Image (spheres, rainbow over the protein chains, first blue to last red):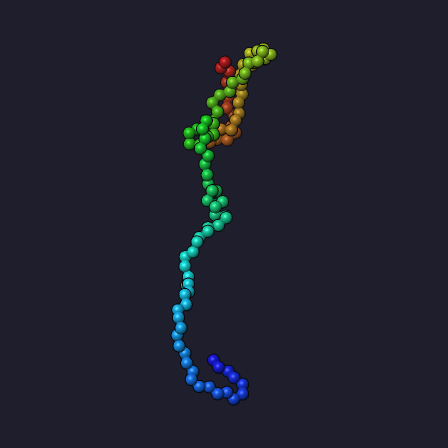
Length: 51
Length: 51
């Protein structure tokens, strides 16, 4: 868009490529699970004992 | 117990000291009441000692 107040003069409007630009979209990332499900995983344990 | 170390009881000695050989040989029967395995805190007999 080109907005200009007061009378303006234009000519020779060019658009032209230069190069490529890298980028990144959306991934399945590192699943650092929690600090809670750890203590919910060990909620069920058993102690092996030598008599 | 093999599947879980819980140590169910089997019997009960009473150690003879030098100063109590008169009192223990004086007691004939023994009345017992304990926490059972699947029942509750039932009472179980008064049977004689076994020495």
